[PDB]
Image 1 (cartoon, rainbow, N blue to C red):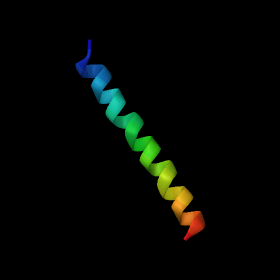
Image 2: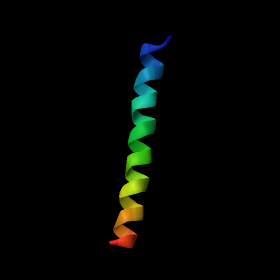
Image 3: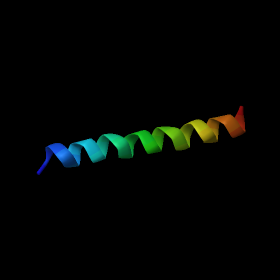
Length: 28
């Protein structure tokens, strides 16, 4: 099963983008 796993991977990358937004919010 790769289609369902790919859906989970897309969500994992989004979590990383959010962590980056919080880091930038603290710096600027």
